[PDB]
Length: 167
Ligand SMILES: [Cl-]
Ligand code: NI
Image (cartoon, rainbow, N blue to C red):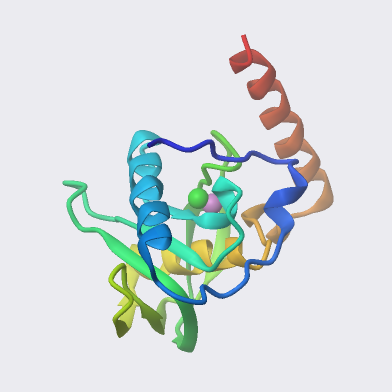
């Protein structure tokens, strides 16, 4: 099923996710719904926080052909290096953008969809998306990296867009 994605200024987006205790049937269903939602929204990543489920679960697909599913359950950042930054969007901040400074390279450990442990070294867009999505799990949004005036403008624009969509 496609789930609702929360938009700013919803306070539930600021909630710090708890670790997943056991990757079970419930967790696998959440993962599958998150993929359905991410693809339906034409996004490249989604955190459980964004769908009002406050557990450390991320789904990602940065591929052009939309056929490279990555699941991070309980991800932990092991190392980071380099400097990068692109214009980022966010499904929770619809249609908005900002240049966000990030690490170019990250190494993480996590559990996959079957609950099997793995490690991953990532760079380029994948590394940027991992960091963006991991931020969500600690209640942090790309807005938080910006000036107060820019944050105000972004909030106002999302609020107007949401009124318009609310039909
Ligand atoms: Cl997002
Ligand atoms: Ni986001």
